[PDB]
Every structure is written in structure tokens, then in C-alpha cells.
Image (tube, rainbow, N blue to C red):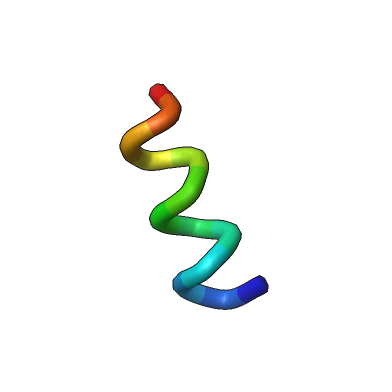
Length: 13
């Protein structure tokens, strides 16, 4: 959610 969902989109982008 917090960093999990955040970092997820980071590397994904």
C-alpha cells in the first residue's frame, strides 16, 4: 500500500 504500492509504480514507470 504505502511504500509497497508506491515503490511498485516507481520501478514500473
